[PDB]
């Protein structure tokens, strides 16, 4: 509460909303911010991306260690504050919604991720050339990011993490650590790019994982029929698809790749 009465002082000094929207959960322990930054190995060469800097507790700690930091904030009066409370030489504040703005070239991400964009952000970052990302998420979501094929909570997000990243939950972060207290705990999650990425088709993975409890012949038939295609013209091919004897939530990325390659061969995704 050295940082929490610092928060309260800033919130009141400018008049900023108690919980801005569902719940903006600002990070307020020095321990946690420093462990994020040390897991990241933020050196003076790095160029860092932060999403949602809030009152900039993490931002300022990143700014004194990295060459440059680009930080993306939706609230315009958080920015107006950031400009006044701080005097960074090496920070570019970027107004916008982190899902929609053009990202910088960066080699690292260290961020307290906004919960409502946890999934879109994860999918965007996963298709970026970064060496190391250290991102706090809600723990339920961080568990889905490391879930394994055939596990119940294995999903699009799981598959795409395993296809493209090395993902580690470093350690739980208690709700105590943010104001206001979330109703659930968080996790310090580490992502590095998989040295040998399995590049899958976005639209095919999306198709498959609308209903993941479905078998993959069923999954495929439904998704392509819904596109407008004749259900007659499509059954034979899709019946003979590789790994037809799995449900979609059982697929390893490699098994999704064979399915793509088969559909590519039979003209179905082109
Ligand atoms: N889509 C978004 N793009 C950029 N900044 C955002 C977005 N959504 C929320 N923010 C900002 O995120 C800052 C603080 C957030 N890191 C807190 C999020 C919190 N950890 C949560 O799990 O909900 C605030 O200043 C918000 O304005
Ligand atoms: Zn749930
Ligand atoms: Zn580690
Ligand atoms: Zn029909
Ligand atoms: Zn198989």
Image: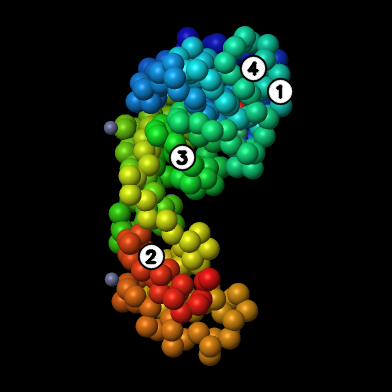
On screen, residue 85 above or below 215: above
Residue 14 spot, x, y in % from top left? 70, 15
User: For mark 4, what is the residue?
Assistant: 82
On screen, residue 247 above or below 149: below
Q: 269 or 2, which is in the foreground?
A: 269
Q: Nearer the viewer, mark 2 or mark 4?
A: 2
Marks 4 and 3 sit apart, C-alpha to C-alpha, by: 28 Å
Residue 257 spot, x, y in % from top left? 38, 64
Q: Nearer the viewer, mark 2 or mark 3?
A: 3
Marks 2 and 3 sit apart, C-alpha to C-alpha, by: 22 Å
Q: Are marks 4 and 3 in contact (CB under 8 Å)?
A: no
Q: 218 or 174, which is in the foreground?
A: 218
Q: Are marks 1 and 4 in contact (CB under 8 Å)?
A: no
Q: Earlier in the sequence, mark 1 or mark 4?
A: 1
Residue 162 spot, x, y in % from top left? 35, 51
Classify 10 Å Cα crowding around label 2: few (below 14), some (14-19), many (20 and above).
many
User: For mark 1, what is the residue?
Assistant: 77
Determine the secondary structure under disc 3: loop
Quadrant of res 169 = top left
Mark 3 Cβ and ligand 3 under 8 Å apart: no
Colour approach in the figure: rainbow
User: For mark 3, what is the residue?
Assistant: 129
Classify 10 Å Cα crowding around label 3: few (below 14), some (14-19), many (20 and above).
few
Q: Earlier in the sequence, mark 3 or mark 1?
A: 1
Specify the label residue 256 is tagged with. 2
Marks 3 and 1 sit apart, C-alpha to C-alpha, by: 31 Å
Q: Nearer the viewer, mark 3 or mark 1?
A: 3
């Amino acid at each position: 509460s050295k940082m929490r009465d610092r928060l309260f002082f800033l919130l009141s000094k400018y008049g900023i909303r108690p919980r801005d929207s569902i719940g903006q959960h600002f990070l307020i322990i020095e321990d946690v911010i420093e462990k994020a930054i040390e897991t990241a190995n933020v050196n003076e060469n790095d160029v860092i991306l932060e999403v949602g800097p809030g009152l900039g507790f993490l931002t300022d700690e990143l700014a004194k260690r990295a060459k440059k930091v680009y930080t993306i904030e939706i609230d315009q009066k958080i920015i107006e504050i950031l400009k006044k409370e701080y005097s960074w030489n090496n920070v570019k504040i970027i107004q916008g919604d982190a899902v929609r703005v053009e990202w910088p070239k960066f080699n690292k991400v260290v961020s307290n991720i906004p919960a409502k964009i946890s999934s879109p952000f994860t999918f965007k970052l996963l298709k970026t050339d970064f060496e190391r990302a250290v991102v706090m998420y809600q723990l339920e979501f961080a568990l889905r990011m490391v879930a394994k094929p055939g596990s119940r909570n294995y999903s699009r997000l799981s598959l795409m993490a395993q296809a493209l990243g090395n993902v580690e939950i470093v350690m739980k972060i208690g709700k105590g650590a943010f104001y206001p207290r979330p109703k659930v705990d968080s996790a310090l999650v580490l992502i590095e790019p998989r040295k040998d990425k399995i590049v899958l088709n976005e639209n095919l993975v999306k198709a498959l994982f609308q209903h993941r409890r479905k078998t993959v012949p069923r999954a495929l038939k439904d998704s392509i029929h819904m596109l407008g295609v004749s259900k007659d013209e499509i059954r034979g091919i899709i019946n003979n698809v590789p790994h037809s004897n799995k449900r979609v939530f059982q697929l390893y990325p490699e098994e999704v790749k064979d399915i793509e390659e088969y559909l590519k061969k039979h003209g179905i995704i082109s």
